[PDB]
Image 1: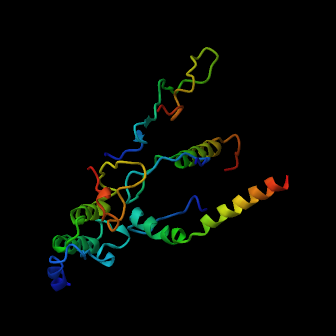
Image 2 (image 1 turned 90 degrees about the horizontal axis):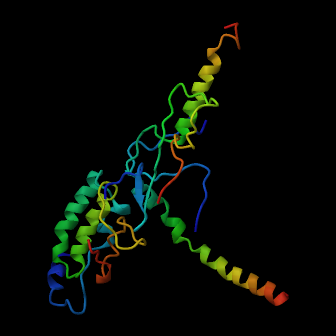
Image 3 (image 1 turned 180 degrees about the vertical axis):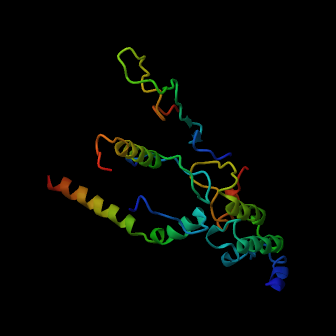
Length: 49
Length: 49
Length: 98
Length: 50
């Protein structure tokens, strides 16, 4: 009786759901977007901008 | 794009939503009939050997 | 319905009067909805005239089914949830210790 | 009966609780060869003590 998931599961408290940002997929998207900010940051890697 | 875009119905309550949604697939009773097939599969392979 | 509710008090021992399933809130109901609030009001007024010995437990657990998600009672086992429909609670082995 | 699953949740006479952050990493930590090891106790979740 066990089921395996590749992502974390923390059960919801309330039953009228609404937004917050404290989950692993938003953490992952935030890390991807800040590293793409770091990649567009350097003038060495793309000087013609 | 399905990860970047997704929303709920505008004012929803989850226990009412799932208590409507899960009801016909438990009114179904197909799952009990497969166990007898599992019986006769195991009995058949044993009596074969 | 009112006159037969008055008549069933003489014949507690053979027939018992209960409230119909359709008078309960639909799909459990919730307190975020005005319709289920009025359903609970009508039901909680109508319950004390029936000769059903589990009518107070039905009166409590109709509200508990509406209230689940916001408040919490303790449950005795890990089988049944607070969000269990109040039609079922009509035999005294289902009365919760809370 | 207070519902808060960010920190603990009960399974019936067994409480689970997410321990975390024995150590804390600063900005100037750069995985240098004389840096003190932190033993993966600076992440979000390294274990779930029951």
